[PDB]
Image (tube, coloured by chain):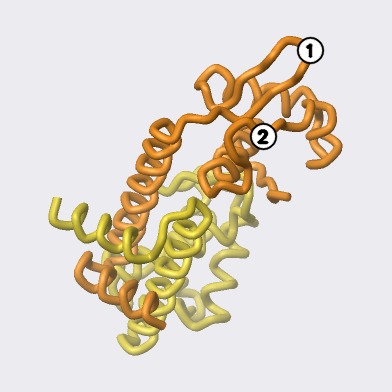
Chain colours: A yellow, B orange
Amino acid sequence: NPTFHADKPIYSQISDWMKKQMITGEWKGEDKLPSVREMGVKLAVNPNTVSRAYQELERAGYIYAKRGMGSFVTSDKALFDQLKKELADAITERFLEEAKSIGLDDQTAIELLIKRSRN
Amino acid sequence: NPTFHADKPIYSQISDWMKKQMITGEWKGEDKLPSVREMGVKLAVNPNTVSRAYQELERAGYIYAKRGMGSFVTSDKALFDQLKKELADAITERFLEEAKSIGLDDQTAIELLIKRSRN
């Protein structure tokens, strides 16, 4: 389970977490998702809040519904590849902004990261 | 001014922000800080909360008091150099953990960052 914080709407944190499960392949295309009530119990979250997260994902095409059969993970490699690209861009943007905020120049930051990556 | 969020104690967010002003040299050694009440008005924050942030910094040696003269930024290049190093390590650690969470491998992440850095 994910852990939630109080700064962002819970439904959006749930959506973010579900997207991560789909991008990493923990949940694969056509996988059947929990009902909103099942997911609420699983996450210890209000099912209304879960519903808002599912609605967000369905609207954006990451999950889809079949009548009287619930919700399923979309199969679309191109769609998930572009999501991963956008999340990756966001991560790099934040890294450089955070570095700037502590006076850590790009060159130094990248070298530190490479060193850490090689352990 | 910094903007505050609801997930972490406000006093610690204030301490974090003040540390950043000192590391980047916006506030230099021996600079006189606002009183806790002045800072509270400046930040639109409860002065009790500001006091907790100042106490945190004084306890750790980043600011110091003179009797009936208020608080001042410590002059100690070695101390601030080590703080910057620790914050930089934390930033790189989080970058790699966040990358892992979206299935972005270290090599790809570093290349993207280098590309972004060169624009």
Which residue corresponds to mark 1? B68
**Which quarter of the figure has residue B39?**
top right
> Do pointers 1 and 2 mark residues of a single chain?
yes
Residue B99 or residue B24, whichever sits in front: B24
> Mark 1 and mark 2: span between their CA atoms?
16 Å
Relative placement, left or right, of A119 versus A38 is: left
Secondary structure state at the residue bearing disc 2: loop
Picture mark count: 2
Subunit of mark 1? B
Is there any visible trace of residue B7 in the rendered image?
no
Left/right of residue A85 with respect to residue B57 in the rendered view: left
Identity of the residue drawn at 81% across and 30% down:
B46
What residue lies at 58% left-to-right and 20% top-to-bottom? B58
Residue A26 location, x and y as percent?
27, 64
**Residue labelled with disc 2:** B31
| Residue occupying image coordinates x 37% and y 45% | B90
Q: Chain of mark 2?
A: B
Expressed as whole percent of the image width and height from the top left, the position of residue A110 reads 30, 63
Point out which mark residue A41 bears. Answer: none
Please indicate, yes or no, whether residue B92 appears anywhere in the rendered image: yes
Above or below residue A118? Residue A81 is below
User: In screen coordinates, is B17 left or right of A117?
Assistant: right
Looking at the image, is B43 positioned above or below residue A26? above
Q: Is residue B85 above or below residue B40?
A: below
Name the spot of residue A34 as percent of width and height, x first. Answer: 43, 61
Q: Nearer the viewer, residue B10 or A45?
A: B10
Query: Residue B81's quadrant in the figure?
Result: top left
Which kind of residue does numbered mark 2 sit on?
Asp
Q: Earlier in the sequence, mark 1 or mark 2?
A: 2
